[PDB]
Amino acid sequence: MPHAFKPGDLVFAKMKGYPHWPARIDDIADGAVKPPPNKYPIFFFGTHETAFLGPKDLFPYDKCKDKYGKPNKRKGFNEGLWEIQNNPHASY
């Protein structure tokens, strides 16, 4: 059975207007802004941007990579596919 999301979990994250995007649940560093209740700090591969999202927008990587892990024209997306497959837990 699945558990709640935790730092380091890999996902495709969905935001309005954009395709499901390779991402990870980030850590929250000491002194860093904490997310709203029931939301998570999402780090987007490729663009290296962060948003606060709830689980309704988070699709687990291993289950959904066949559908969502394919080249896309958007800027930064295929760089992001490389990051999530080859070094998803590194500092960018």
Image: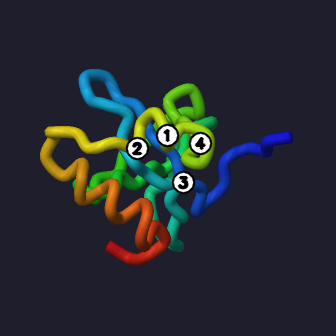
Residue drawn at point x = 74 percent, y = 44 percent = 4
Q: Say whether disc 2 or disc 4 marks the residue closer to the N-terminus.
A: 4
Please, what is the three-letter code of the amino acid marked with disc 3?
Leu
Alpha carbon distance from label 2 to label 1? 6 Å
Q: Position of residue 18 (x, y in %)?
A: 27, 29
Q: Residue at x 42, y 51 (%)?
A: 23
The quarter holding residue 68 reads top left
In screen coordinates, is 68 left or right of 55? left
Left or right: 44 as drawn, with respect to 78? right
Task: Provide residue 8's location: percent of width, then percent of height.
Answer: 58, 62
Q: How would you rate the neighbour count of disc 1 (Cα within 10 Å): few for under 14, some for 14-19, many for 20 or more? A: few
92 horizontally vs 57: left or right? left
Residue 69 is marked as 2
Q: Are marks 3 and 2 in contact (CB under 8 Å)?
A: no
Circle nearer the N terminus (3, 2)? 3
Give the residue at mark 4: 60
Q: In the drawing, does residue 47 fall left or right of residue 89?
A: left
Category of crowding for the residue at label 3, using alpha-carbon neighbours closer than 10 angstroms: few (below 14), some (14–19), many (at least 20): many
Which quarter of the image is occupied by the C terminus?
bottom left
Residue 11's spot in the image, x, y percent?
51, 46
